[PDB]
Image 1 (tube, rainbow, N blue to C red):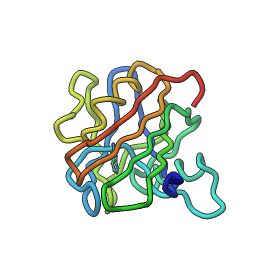
Image 2: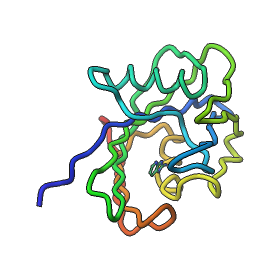
Image 3: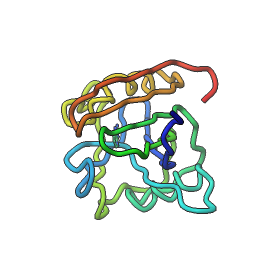
Length: 158
Ligand SMILES: Nc1nc2ncccc2[nH]1
């Protein structure tokens, strides 16, 4: 039948030449895993404006240019609504990251990406982000640990 309906999300990675900023999710779904900063796009908001707002809310950072780098769709067994995640990168930030109720920011060297404490799908697409390639992905999860199906492709546009 028809693809499930999807909810629009953003995800921002501050990626510098030798390190990347992640945040430890402190509560709710995905707590205990390092992730980029993001959340649901609000009514009337552009995707990029939502990305900037979520970055500021969760990490305290404001940034200049955000670059579109990929799109990931997540599906969970037992939930009909999908997550449509628009992924952005930036390399130039203004200020110091600050812990929020949602996220504890932390820098990681690029030879110390904490995959064991990240979502399982990151093993597949996060390397593409690091290579500066654009991608579309889809992952179907049983619970929080098990991937039942996934697709991933590199693209020139997205
Ligand atoms: N990397 C990543 N973030 C996620 N958020 C929610 C569900 C699955 C996820 N995979």
